[PDB]
Amino acid sequence: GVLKEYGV
Amino acid sequence: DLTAFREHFAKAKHIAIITGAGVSAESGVPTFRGPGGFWRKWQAQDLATPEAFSRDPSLVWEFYHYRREVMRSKMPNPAHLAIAECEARLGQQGRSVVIITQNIDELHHRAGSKHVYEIHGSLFKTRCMSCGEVKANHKSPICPALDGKGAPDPNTKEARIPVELLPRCERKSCNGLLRPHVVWFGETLDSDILTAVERELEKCDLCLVVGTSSIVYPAAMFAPQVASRGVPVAEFNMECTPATKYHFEGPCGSTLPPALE
Ligand SMILES: [Zn+2]
């Protein structure tokens, strides 16, 4: 599942 | 060219509108990210995480209570309204408009939009940490112990509310601690929501990106898929472009009502 803001 | 965009708009049967923080900043709604995006000593990165909530749930709830309370005076802007009225008008003609929003302020709903996917959650929903139930909640104050709390000044004293008196789940058996139903830094976006968004983006024949950019997130997750079907993308944002799809520079509450009329 997708990580809010790609983890940045 | 607005004329060329409007020629696509006149023909589009399925419009997907993605909206980011620019459209909510224009309603006066603090993001807490960047220079002066402080609440007490903290920025949003510090607080919108499960680690903050685990270690100091009272502090995190004070922050979210402040945000919930500040929404009462903040109002949808002409961009939100244009989008909502466009959806209503086109819907009567059998044409679909859907909003995919990063914003948790519910301003799109207050504007009148029906078909809205809130990919980061909502300030006005809770989730129970025990039974998982998601529930709408617009109460001011959300619980009595938070009444008058959440002041944003650096030197405000912490309320230090015992966890038992923070918002609790009202299923009589359960009583679990509630958290905001907002996606925090380090958490996954909801898979079901993303599947629904993918279906809408795949069916759409014109896509607008408002108060953010196609090139960053969340637009970057879906916009390439749309572009590669040959579908026009139109950005409305205050960001510049060099000498180099469509980009309408400026505040969305100015540009968008003209584009969508
Ligand atoms: Zn519960």
Image (spheres, helix red, strand yellow):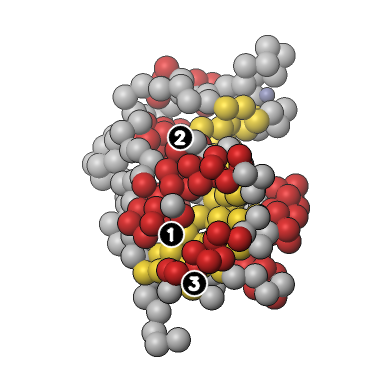
**Residue linked to disc 1:** B259
Question: Is B226 rendered above or below residue B110?
Answer: below
| Left or right: B255 in relation to B194 | left
Query: Residue B53 versus residue B6: which sits nearer the camera?
Result: B6
Label of residue B93 in the image: none
**Residue linked to disc 2:** B110
Query: Residue B47 versus residue B257: which sits nearer the camera?
Result: B257
Query: Residue B29 versus residue B244: which sits nearer the camera?
Result: B244
Label of residue B4 in the image: 3
Q: Nearer the viewer, mark 3 or mark 1?
A: 3
The picture quadrant where one finds residue B70 is: top left
- Dot 2: element: helix
| Left or right: B59 in relation to B173 | left
The picture quadrant where one finds residue B173 is: top right
- Amino acid carrying label 1: it is Ala
The picture quadrant where one finds residue B146 is: top left
C-alpha span from label 3 to label 1: 11 Å
| Residue at (62, 32) in percent of width and height | B127
Which residue extends farthest bottom?
B243
x, y (%) of residue B229? 71, 72
- Amino acid carrying label 2: it is Arg
Q: Write down the chain letter for disc 1.
A: B
- Amino acid carrying label 3: it is Ala
| Residue at (28, 57) in percent of width and height | B36
Name the N-terminal-most of marks 2 and 3: 3
Asked if disc 2 is less than 8 Å from ligand 1, the answer is no
C-alpha span from label 2 to label 3: 31 Å
| Residue at (62, 16) in percent of width and height | B170
x, y (%) of residue B213? 49, 68
Q: Is residue B104 visible?
A: no
Q: Nearer the viewer, mark 2 or mark 3?
A: 3
